[PDB]
Structures are given as C-alpha cells and as structure tokens.
Amino acid sequence: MFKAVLFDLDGVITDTAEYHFRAWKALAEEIGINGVDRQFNEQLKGVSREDSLQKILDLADKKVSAEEFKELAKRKNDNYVKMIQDVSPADVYPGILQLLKDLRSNKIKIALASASKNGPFLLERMNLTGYFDAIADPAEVAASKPAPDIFIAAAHAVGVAPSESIGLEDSQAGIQAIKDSGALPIGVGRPEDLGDDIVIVPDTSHYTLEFLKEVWLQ
Ligand SMILES: [Mg+2]
Image (cartoon, rainbow, N blue to C red; front, top):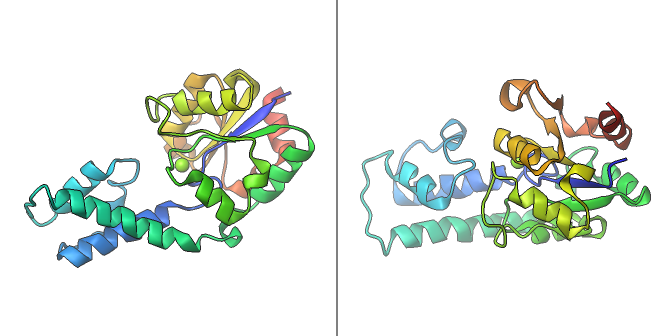
C-alpha cells in the first residue's frame, strides 16, 4: 500500500491562478496597457514574473526603465498577496477535505509539493495545516517542474521514497515531475492536456481514498 500522498496546491486543492490573473490584470490597467484577459493569461501561467511582465509590456510596445520593471513586478506581487488574504476554508476543492481526513485516519502521510511561495499561509487560511505532515519549500529545491525535485523533497520530508507515494496534479509539467521522481501520478483534468498514458479523473470530487487505493493495486 502507498505510504503517502503528495499534493499540488493550485488546481488540485484550490484555485490560486484566479488571484494571479487579477494581479496581472490590475497591473496592466494601472499602467495603461490593453487586453490582459484569461486567454492571454494562459501565456503567463507557469512562468516567472520577469517573462510575464515582458509579455504584458509587449502588448503595446511599452518600454520601461529598470528601476520600474523592478517596481512593476513588485506591485503585482504586493497585489496578489493583498488579494489572497480572503482565501477561506470555503475555497477548498470538493472531496479534498474528506480525502485528507481519510488519509490522516488510515495513517497515510500528507505532504505538499506545490511551486507556491505562499503554501503554508494558504493551508492555514483554508484550515488544512492539521493534516499535512510536511510542506516542500520550493526555495530550498534547486529546480522547478517539470523537474522531479519538489516531489522528492515532499516525500523525503515525511520519510518515504517517491515510489511509496502517489502525486496529485493538474498540469503536464506537474505530471512529468511526479513521473521522474518515481511516484504514481493521478491527474485532474483532460487527457488532451495531461496524457492518456496515466490515470485522470474529471474533477477533484473523484479523488477518493477508495479510488486512490484501486489505482495503486492496478
Ligand atoms: Mg497545478
């Protein structure tokens, strides 16, 4: 039997991508740049501030200083942090709380393997800290996803190998990072996005303990 589950935060446990989008949208406006919508935001999604800002600045040929590019990148970060202050337990995805409880009661270790720099904060605010044995610190890991480093750290931090674990993810980079750690991925989303060589549920309601068990035995 699997001895742990390693959780992605965004798109599995909750939606942090909504607040990111509004921070970049807000900045776009307060500058005068046009048309930062949700379709465009798919270019900003798994990418660092610098490139995101570069793409947002190219929508109107806007040239910036440097002591200004630094500032504009900092405004988006200040704004994201304002906006996530209202994350509540009411934002926990369906079936996640119940899965975590069933996991705590069956003595399966629970670890976070998210890119997010606000991971513990977001878990406090949603009232899920009690369930997690460890949180992978993405500043301590040398490389990001699709590298397997954050899933390895996540397992190690709860005293297991990746191969004793299942990873929960919603992105192709995330799936490939679970795969290279040696963990068993179970996707959330479309196999058009994530791949038909792995097991995927439509949404997080379908992440049950019983289902997780059936997948391991297969
Ligand atoms: Mg994700």
